[PDB]
Amino acid sequence: KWKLFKKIPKFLHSAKKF
């Protein structure tokens, strides 16, 4: 399987920054 939409770490970096 694949998940490039999860490879982006800067994304989860905003999750905790929100």
Image (cartoon, helix red, strand yellow):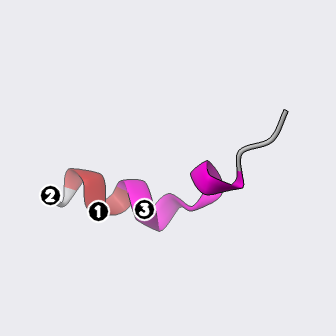
Vertical comparison of 18 with 3: above or below: below
| Disc 2 residue type (three-letter) | Phe
The residue positioned 29% from the left and 62% from the top of the image is 14
Is 1 or 9 nearer to us in this picture?
A: 1
Pick out the residue farthest to the left. 18
Pick out the residue farthest to the bottom. 10
Q: Earlier in the sequence, mark 3 or mark 2?
A: 3
**Disc 1/disc 2 C-alpha distance (Å):** 6 Å
Pick out the residue farthest to the right. 1
Tell me, yes or no, whether the two marked residues, 1 and 2, touch with CB atoms within 8 Å.
yes
Label of residue 11 in the image: 3
Vertical comparison of 2 with 6: above or below: above
Residue at image mark 1: 14
Q: Is residue 5 left or right of residue 10?
A: right
The residue positioned 51% from the left and 59% from the top of the image is 9
**Disc 1/disc 3 C-alpha distance (Å):** 5 Å
Q: Which residues are magenta?
A: 4-12
Image x and y of residue 10, in percent: 45, 67
Q: Under tag 1, what secondary structure?
A: helix
Mark 3 neighbour density, 10 Å: few (under 14) some (14–19) many (20 or more) = few
Image x and y of residue 1, in percent: 85, 32
Let me know if residue 9 is in the magenta part: yes
Q: Main secondary structure of the magenta part?
A: helix
Label of residue 18 in the image: 2
Tell me, yes or no, whether the two marked residues, 1 and 3, touch with CB atoms within 8 Å.
yes
**Disc 3/disc 2 C-alpha distance (Å):** 11 Å
